[PDB]
Image (cartoon, rainbow, N blue to C red):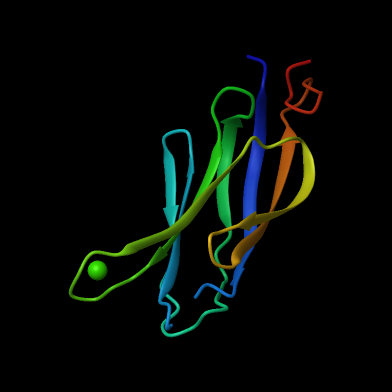
Length: 122
Ligand SMILES: [Ca+2]
């Protein structure tokens, strides 16, 4: 099958998210899902998570979706914002502007052998 790649997403951090924020991320690609921990009381959080999505369909299986949530203990959490990317092969630094502030992360996408092209369709 064409369009297949290894996808690893990392180096998650956010800026100016507010007035106190308790942020965590949910990160999706196709049917797969990761969730980070909560950084309590911080408008510029960083998370150490490395998210290996292993083999994915880079073309059709997307998008890569990052949700930035504010944990509210004893109530419903607040969705601060969300962004989508259609990943391309290589190494990429993403900046997602939110209504307030932004979230940043990197990803590496490498086509499976005998595939090439920016979305591994060739
Ligand atoms: Ca809650």
